Image (spheres, coloured by chain):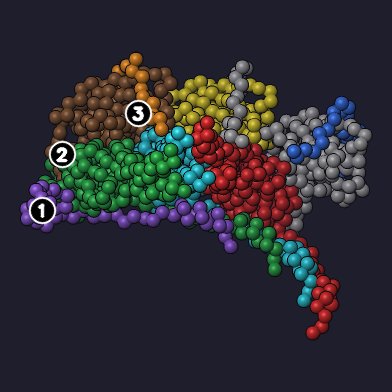
Chain colours: A red, C yellow, D cyan, E green, F purple, G brown, H orange, J blue
């Protein structure tokens, strides 16, 4: 039995204390591709979000280590990834999980488990939207066309329901220029080392 | 938003040899 | 042996062997120079698309016997990772990156010529069923 | 009794840390067909998604190992697969599970358990859609034609319900040029080896 | 109390790793009919999906082993199968389970437990559809005909009744039809090879 | 916490493997009427 | 014996044996050359469709006695995997890949000729019931 | 559903320009 | 060794080595001077954008072979952290901060020149596969 | 809809390097 008003206020004056954070240092900057670098790619597979499946792209240009001094993700590497859901109305791009990079000269493989982007780094591969309007409307249209020819709302409300049951689908051409946002540090320490010359 | 327009097709009005010089296989 | 695996591997890493064909032509459009190849040729088995050493790698598609543009298999060769060696040979090709495209036509497509019955890319290494 | 607003905010400033990833190297690149390579195929069986069942195709051209040097999936091989569900309105292609490749010269078999595609890599085999409009409409049409010949709200809404109960079906001719996205590394190590000459 | 948004995204970045797969070799290719081969057949029994039951067909032409070298499923063999469900509106073909092949010269029997097809390999045997429209409509028609003659809902009930009776499929006796071998069929224990 | 979409797809790539089947031979073919033969009949009762 | 299984197997691996028939004609449409065969011939038992060594393998269908186009059974032979040996013989065929089609007609279809009663593809190896 | 194309036989031509050989 | 890792690291921290290119031009708009670079030049491998010592660092984008403005990778060099060394070379560039933009064009883009096949940014240090 | 960032105006284009840079 202390005042409720009083307690609520006391509670709102009690913040969640955030923990301070300690800086440290990256262990192998010459042998690491760190979070936030971009891997520019050109898609091998065409893409169509009607049925969930897989995608490939091939690294377009070399990507260097955290300090920019060592080549680590080689141009011409193959990347395999998956597109496992589709798009909704109001969307013109889709989430893409790029899984593994495989250098085909060398055999170096790394699970990057990173998201695909644009060339400018925003999330998802952009594409062309097919709204499937005709298929989403034809039933109601056909039916009502009788109702009309039956003459000289609830249907309409059922129509909209049916209209929403089929999604738009996204297409993107083969060979598109596209990118990957590196989501996690990629450590090449166990694979490459350095020597003169 | 019906369908999908396919990627561009080349224009061949001006067609040209690829090899200005003979390539070499370096193995 | 480990030393045997190494010799066979090096030997094999050498065949794009055989009579070569250089008879290739391409569409020429100025907007598309940024993905044009410097060379295209073949072996009658595999086809090489060579780009400038530091150029971005575009992607390559083939026109199949079926009439359709088709995604083939390929690997890069070269110190500069600038040559796409496609694991196949074809009458016609597309080079693509984003909305740039370059048509490439093989004026001496001769399926029928140049097979090797070895089970590898090379005339000198053979695949053996254990 | 710390502030709820404060806690919600503190929680939203606490990210899920992603684990760094270590590069490695592929074990037998000359004797492996790796993820992402395409197996071009020509369908043997015609395809009709009315009743779930099986499909075959025969590999159209050789497929080489990870480094391009060894022929592993031989032109002429037969692939058996299954199409176990159908299509929905707004779709013109269907998920296909390709199960095993069998070399009929040699006896080499491998379970690829991989998804069928287009020639250009996008998911599912394209086909020709039969929307079954007449069968999906005839009940309502027939019935209302009396109601009208009684000219001489819920029916329509019932109609649309019935309209949705039957799916469109997909057909694709025999001998279609089609492809398979290798989903998982295929290791031929135990079957093939190399020798000069 | 890590961010939900953050977790949802981390989870969407974590793929289900697929296992690699090892190639092997088929044990008795000359004595096996492998998955995917077609058995062409001519139906003995007429077929009618009104009542679940059985079908038979007779192998139309020899089917050889995995490598093409040995005759294994002999022309003239009888196959017994079942059709245990019907068709729905919007279908003109039905699932058929072929159970056993029986060579009547020889006695060789094998349970193929495989699905019947077209001559071109697509699923189910095609047939001729009887929609039963009259039976599916006569009640409502008759009733409303009074309602009409009365005055000179039901409709929604009608459609309900309309959906309770399925179309049925018929296919003539002697149809040219096929079977997609679903599973490898091993004749190793029954046949062997000798010159000459 | 692996991706749901990723699992759903991995699951759809995992077929139910069918068992191979072994041919055998029928024991007494001269003294057996086997599945699939027809017995033509004339009904007695209506 | 293991050595016996090997001899019988080789022996058998040789029969497309027998009087041969080469009397085949085909539709000729220039859009369809990319899947045309170089040879078609038969044994009176099996039919071979031979394609250029490095050509893509199209698919083959038969016109059955029923009048319907039909999916037959077939395996590939040759070092180049370029010959489709169909395990049957027929008056008429279709070769198909994508939308390309080639009609092939057999001008000396003689069912009735060429059977072997051996239980195998070969006159020299026989199937025996254990 | 439209079935796959049918050949045009206006110009019919022999398949074998030369006699094949069985290399087994 | 720890001393060996230190020598290699220093050696490497020296290459923007090579023939240099200075042939760069830029749009000149007075509103955009606040993000203009003092120098732009390259190596035929990497490209340097140099800004006044204490100026705010703007961000830099390349025009790719595909025709699209693209986000590259890059690190800063210099005691004053005022040089952006982009890990790539290109025909054309954008410098952006907020709604400020400066176009920067490379009048001697020569992909094909200047590659090193070393596996590092340097001609003198090489990447080795353990 | 979403308007993209400004593009430069090249009416007046000008060399970047008034002096030659040095790699320190």
Residue F23 image offset from top left, x and y in percent: 21, 53
For the residues labelled 3 and 2, the Cα–Cα distance comes to 31 Å
Do tags 2 and 1 sit on the same chain?
no
Cβ–Cβ under 8 Å for marks 3 and 2: no
The numbered mark at residue F45 is 1
Q: Residue at x 66, y 36 (%)?
A: C56
For the residues labelled 2 and 1, the Cα–Cα distance comes to 59 Å
Left/right placement of residue E74 relative to residue A31 reads left
Do tags 1 and 3 sit on the same chain?
no
Count the marks: how many?
3
Q: Residue at x 20, y 46 (%)?
A: E56
The numbered mark at residue G124 is 2
Chain hosting mark 3:
G
Chain hosting mark 2:
G
Residue D73 image offset from top left, x and y in percent: 41, 43
Residue F30 image offset from top left, x and y in percent: 6, 53
Note whether residue A105 is visible. no
The numbered mark at residue G95 is 3
Residue A93 image offset from top left, x and y in percent: 64, 43
> Which mark is first along the chain, 2 or 3?
3
Residue extending farthest to the left is: F30
């Amino acid at each position: 039995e202390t005042s409720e008003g009083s307690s609520a206020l006391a509670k709102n004056l009690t913040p969640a204390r955030l923990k301070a954070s300690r800086a440290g240092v990256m262990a192998n900057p010459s042998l690491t591709v760190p979070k936030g670098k971009m891997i520019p790619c050109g898609t091998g597979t065409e893409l169509d979000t009607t049925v969930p499946g897989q995608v490939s792209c091939r690294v377009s240009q070399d990507v260097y280590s955290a300090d920019g001094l060592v080549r680590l993700i080689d141009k011409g590497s193959w990347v395999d990834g998956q597109i496992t859901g589709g798009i909704k109305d109001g969307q013109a791009r889709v989430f893409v999980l790029w899984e593994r990079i495989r250098n085909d000269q060398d055999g170096t493989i790394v699970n990057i488990d990173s998201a695909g982007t644009n060339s400018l780094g925003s999330a998802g591969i952009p594409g062309q939207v097919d709204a499937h309007m005709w298929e989403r409307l034809r039933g109601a249209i056909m039916i009502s066309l009788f109702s009309d020819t039956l003459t000289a709302g609830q249907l309409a409300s059922e129509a909209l329901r049916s209209y929403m049951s089929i999604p738009p689908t996204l297409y993107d051409q083969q060979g598109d220029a596209v990118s990957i946002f590196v989501a996690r540090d990629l450590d090449f320490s166990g694979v490459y080392t350095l020597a003169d010359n | 938003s019906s369908g999908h327009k396919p990627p561009p097709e080349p224009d061949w009005s001006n067609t040209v040899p690829v090899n200005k010089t003979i390539p070499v296989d370096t193995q | 042996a480990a030393d045997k695996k190494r010799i066979t591997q090096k030997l094999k890493q050498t065949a794009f062997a055989g009579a070569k064909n250089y008879q290739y032509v391409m569409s020429e459009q100025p907007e598309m120079r940024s993905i044009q190849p410097v060379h295209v040729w073949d072996n009658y088995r595999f086809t090489r698309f060579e780009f400038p050493a530091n150029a971005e790698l575009p992607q390559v598609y083939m026109i199949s016997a079926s009439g359709k543009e088709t995604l083939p298999n390929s690997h890069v060769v070269g110190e500069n990772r600038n040559i796409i060696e496609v694991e196949t040979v074809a009458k016609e090709w597309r080079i693509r990156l984003g909305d740039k495209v370059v048509g490439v036509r093989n004026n001496n497509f001769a399926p029928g010529r140049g097979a090797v019955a070895t089970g590898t890319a090379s005339p000198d290494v053979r695949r053996v069923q254990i």
